[PDB]
Image (cartoon, rainbow over all chains, first blue to last red; front, side):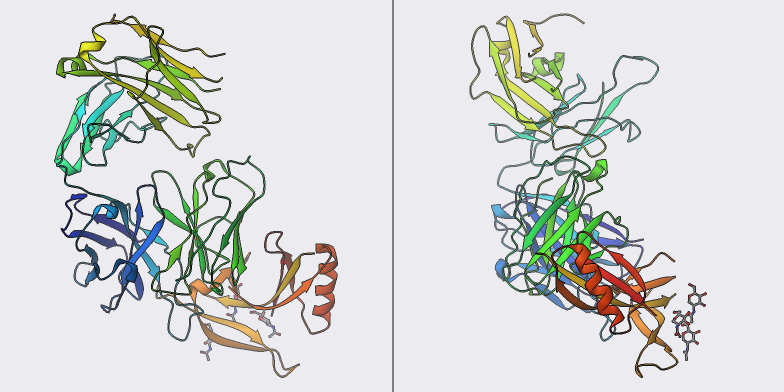
Length: 210
Length: 206
Length: 103
Ligand SMILES: *[C@@H]1O[C@H](CO)[C@@H](O)[C@H](O)[C@H]1NC(C)=O
Ligand SMILES: *[C@@H]1O[C@H](CO)[C@@H](O)[C@H](O)[C@H]1NC(C)=O
Ligand SMILES: *[C@@H]1O[C@H](CO)[C@@H](O)[C@H](O)[C@H]1NC(C)=O
């Protein structure tokens, strides 16, 4: 019943301030740890902090004072705010829920992170943003920054059997990757097949017909 | 600050089998240990909490035991979807709840030279596609006219599909149109498993 | 070689704030009318059973150090006869743990 949905920047520059916002659908704040966890691109999970409906917070010291969370009673959302951003902060960021027991009644004071938001990729660098170029085959999106890029087919309908690959960093300082599909034999006409490609960081959505 | 230490790192071990994943708290953490599973295009989902209790939802084929300092998630009756990463989190000592660094759980060749548009812009890259490995360990070398390309080929690697088996590879050779307009044979040499290595030349037909 | 646990588990009859109201049979005196009684629980603290019935996450446990799971079976079943423990005998090959559900 609980939906977690986050959103925010995804690219920003050293010294600045990251800001992310999780909104909770189907339930409320009631004595849960509303948490923030991140994973550097090929790294370990790192616990950032958490807040409960009070305003009570607990941040990870090993981040000095940089991290700060807040909560917004009205809308059922809460929000991460990292200060003085630097390159290591490039990581996927998740909002998550942890239940905190019940004073007296409960065995423990923490049950898992049971509920996780979809994730927000946040890339810190000086480089500016460039939408990809889309070159049909199959589908090819090339030369974009930063991560990541959206690949859906026929406004979502077409789905099955794909191997949409991981991004490959080029020497040009710009990422690029390759999206395939597997539909053997033919039936070339009758059905028309389009790749939806979206690149939030740079306001680029191409519906390039293949 | 408790430090979590999983041990096997990787296990690409065969289905149906019994597997024992370890986790080791550097300190005594009673039974405050949870286990997370991480799928591909997915966030972590909660498997076992309280060192031993299955999270509401996750099937009984998962077994988390342990207490004090050495812990274990354990799976046996594997479904296909079970390839993923498996992380453990301690929650006795905090600030820093701390996680462990995890445990990680013949091909088919194709080839693809550029379209009209990729050329008309400036440079052109030729990519090949290794649909479905078993296993992923391989070397794929681009060559043009009894040569070998070094430094101008990039590599892409997928992680095992859940609703199937397998891996998948994506190499790419990056040069300018002042180099694709020329030259003859363009070979993607996929070694293992004797190799059929598709190609094309100079520009051709529809 | 290996260490075996045995959990002696009070069965719970129960039926969202995470609270569940539940009833179970407690002892003391060592042969009362076996007393049905009502306590409050945290829903995440009870695990289901094949019926709606529940057991707590952790229980009062005894540990043996057997030669084999077979010998440990005896030892526990003997230990249970010795103290007034009768119920469902289930066992896990991954926990190496015998759970008995009383009440
Ligand atoms: C004990 O619990 C049951 C079910 O919760 C209820 O029917 C009964 O009234 C309770 N007894 C008291 C004294 O509250
Ligand atoms: C115990 O649970 C059963 C169902 O399994 C129910 O019929 C019965 O009324 C319950 N008794 C009490 C005292 O709650
Ligand atoms: C134990 O409790 C069950 C239901 O929880 C009940 O059916 C049974 O009568 C109880 N045993 C006693 C009171 O000795």
